Amino acid sequence: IGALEDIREELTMAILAPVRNPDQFKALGLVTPAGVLLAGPPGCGKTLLAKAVANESGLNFISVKGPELLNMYVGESERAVRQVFQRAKNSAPCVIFFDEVDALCPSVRVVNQLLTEMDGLEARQQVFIMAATNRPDIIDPAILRPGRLDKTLFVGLPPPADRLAILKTITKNGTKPPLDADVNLEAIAGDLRCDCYTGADLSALVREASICALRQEMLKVSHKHFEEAFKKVRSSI
Image 1 (tube, rainbow, N blue to C red):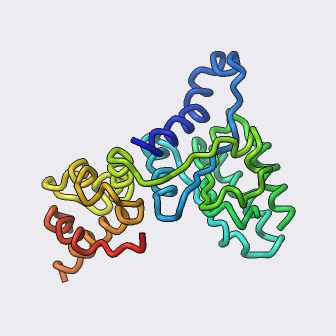
Image 2 (image 1 turned 90 degrees about the vertical axis):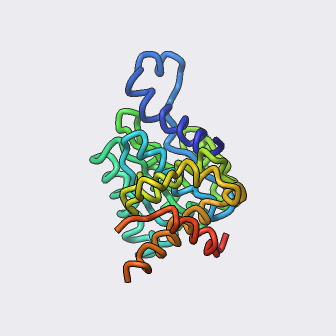
């Protein structure tokens, strides 16, 4: 275990522990932060581990792409910010992922609306931010100040436990793609060639195996597919 176990603990202490033990939580002087910052090179599985942790805890997940939110310059951007926080509150417990939070926080007012909405959040509301960047030294240190995205989590090469978690999310626990009984994800995650794997190679491993399964038909994903997929992992990471 590596980054998975860290992301797991930060969610429980902001969406499970404060609701389940309010008198104990508020007695230790604990205050839920708006979110966490995921930092590391792209393709390491920041998004997949965020979705993995939400799933296993029975939480909702709402994504936001940093460059996509520049739809209406200053305009509908702030209204979208406001809607994503609103959407998350109606579908609580929910996690609001700000993918590529950098360069969105390098408009000088959307940072204030992001800080507004983050400061506007309470533990009762059961909403947890997860932001992602490849360069934390470039983001606004305002969004990183205590109460906001105060705990930074570094995501590097996933250890064997993070790989099975990533695989249980990509395959949606062997339902999308549907896996047959001969496929043991725990054996795939612990494989020799997976020890150097990024989140992207795991993501490509499932695609390639699924592509094999769709290519043969021209439905389930077999160990044979995963075997042929390892010979085809030409992931950009």
